[PDB]
Length: 231
DNA sequence: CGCTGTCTCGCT
DNA sequence: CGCTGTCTCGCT
DNA sequence: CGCTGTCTCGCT
Image (cartoon, rainbow, N blue to C red; front, side, top):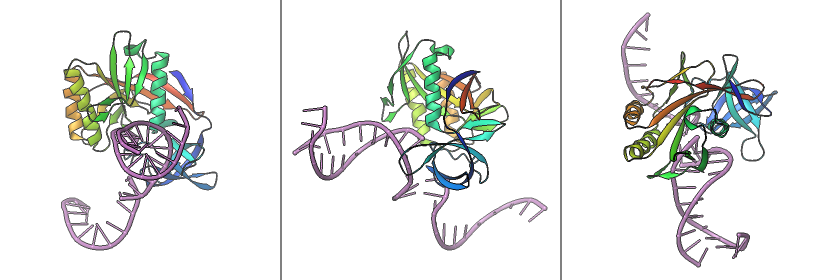
């Protein structure tokens, strides 16, 4: 339980509906407002008229707010994948992760094959390719991925398979940005092949980790440690 | 994802 | 498709 | 470098 960073200001909202995959309508202080959604997943378990969400204002654009997360067991599940990215950057920088206790980000969205992976990190040892994925689909004590078929996600895992096999370091970090979870596993029904490809990748030396994060009402983003991975 | 309009399922 | 926001191109 | 205008990218 380390404090990673704070989101300010942070406002409770009532979720009304999605206008489209990038925009939700929320009610804040009697007013109806448009909120950016940065998470391509379905989030059907979260995106239900009436549930309490949490937003933060921004300047400009076609939306005045960013929908960051939802009430979940008294705290906050973080659905915003840019915020998840920042919390992961902070983890690296502060060296709170055992696998990377002295490393730095040298490139973001570095090109591999005909795709782009998330990070190129530099260890004391050598070069490492880290891809992150949002795991906010719950089953009991498990945070899971995905909640729908991701053809983009298949090909990304393949690049990690094609890199590892061919003598390169390749990692995948599932961000379990839910409170009250201690394990990760893939949701087979969400995508049949990503389950398969995860074992295939796990066999080819591709490191697979999963982290536990939540947000408090204060806006405080908390890292809870690694989740037990069960690929 | 939600977008239109229409057409499809088993179990109660 | 258009939907957000921010990113990337060559040639002039 | 910034200069015009237009046309190009993946990921969210």
